[PDB]
Every structure is written in C-alpha cells, then in structure tokens.
Image: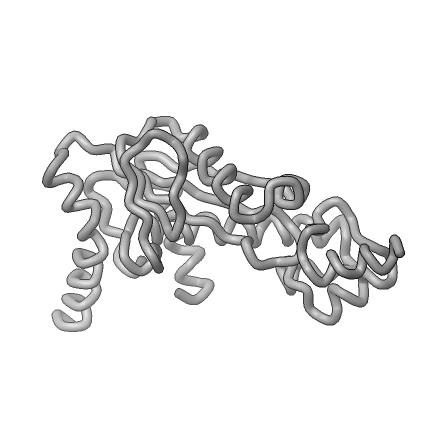
Amino acid sequence: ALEKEQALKEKYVEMTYFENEILKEHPNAIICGIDEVGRGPLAGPVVACATILNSNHNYLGLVPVTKRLELNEALKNEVTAFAYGIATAEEIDEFNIYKATQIAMQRAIDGLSVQPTHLLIDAMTLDNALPQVSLIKGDARSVSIAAASIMAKVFRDDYMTQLSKDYPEYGFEKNAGYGTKQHLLAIDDIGIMKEHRKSFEPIKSLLLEHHH
C-alpha cells in the first residue's frame, strides 16, 4: 500500500515541475493553469477554464467519470480561484476556432477573483502581457493545467446536456456536439440552430450547396 501510493505522490510532484520552477524564481507567484475543451465538436461553445490552485494543493489522481466528478467537486471546494471562459458558436464562426479559443481563455482569466502573475497554458499563447508557458499535452505536464481541463470538461458536458433538453433531436446529451450520423441526420431533418458552427465542415459545405 505504501508503493502504489508513492507512485501517485511521485507523479504529482513531477506534474508540479513547472509551477515549482516559477516559484523558485518568484515565491510571490500567483500561478494560473488554463485549458479548453470543445475545439472539435460541430456544435456548442468552446469552454476554457482558468484555475489557481491553493498553495497546499494535493489533488492526487489529477481519468474515468466517477474520478472526474470527484476531482471536479474537490477542486471547486478548495482551489484559490477558478473561472470559466465561453466563446459561442457564433464567435467561433466569426473569429475561427483558434482565435475563439484565445477569447475564451482570456475570458476565463478576467473572471478570476485574483489576477494571476504567471500562466501555464495547454498548447496556446495569449497576446496578453503576462509571463506564460505554453505546453504540449499541458494537462499531463502540469497539475494547474490538469485541474483546469477537468473543470472545463464537466462544465461543457453539463452545458451540452442542458442543451439536449431544449433540442432533443440532435442527440447532444450523447454526442456533446460531435457530428455523428444521428446529429447529421437531425440537421438534414430540421436544419441547424444557433449552437451549430457554420464554419465547420460538414455544415460548411452543406450550406454552400443549399445556397447554390
């Protein structure tokens, strides 16, 4: 029992590498992790979360659904700060999904009770004037980022679940907006709605042929 437990602790410390390097140079640092979900679906918002972990954070296990829900509630109960940033399907169509994701991440920063001094970000740079580290597979490299992605995930899934109540035909509660055959057949049947991303294929090409 002291082994498997050691492994989780050891993993957790490796995943604090980047916060610890910053802290070494700045013990003052207010370190905020940022991740997003929802870049891939055909429908729904893109949802970013920004989180500053409490200094004595020890969310070991930072991923199946029971575990995700547990950590989601633990983080919400003990973290120094967290806030969600949303960019709508319309903004995604206007700005493209990359840029809409940047808007979502900054919106997440603005909603924080505490302004961060440093950002750890999953595969993204933000124009804002802050020091930041963009990390590939950030959610596996940083506890702050992993927390953010978990919280973003639960939020977006809850959102799409709420959506499926008002729009049952598209199958949102099951597909979370991905363009499955069911989702695409619903579109063929009753058309798109305000959560659909017009800039995303296969909708993009379907709108063309319709206008032609």
Where is residue 188? Give x, y as percent: 84, 63
In this image, 66 relative to 6: left or right?
right
Which residue is pictured at 54% across the width and 54% down the height? 39
Q: Position of residue 210 (x, y in %)?
A: 87, 57
Query: Is residue 180 positioned above or below 204 on the image?
Result: below
* Viewer-proximal residue among 66 and 126: 126
Q: Residue at x 38, y 31 (%)?
A: 128
- Looking at the rendering, in which quadrant would you find the C terminus? bottom right
In the displayed structure image, the side of residue 71 where residue 56 appears, left or right: left
Residue 143 placement (x, y as % from top left): 28, 52
The image quarter in which residue 66 lies: bottom left
Above or below, comparing residue 2 to residue 71 in the picture: below
Residue sitting at the far front: 212
Please state, as top left, top right, bottom left or bottom right, where the N terminus lies in the image: bottom left
Q: How is this picture coloured?
A: one colour
Q: Position of residue 78 (x, y in %)?
A: 32, 40
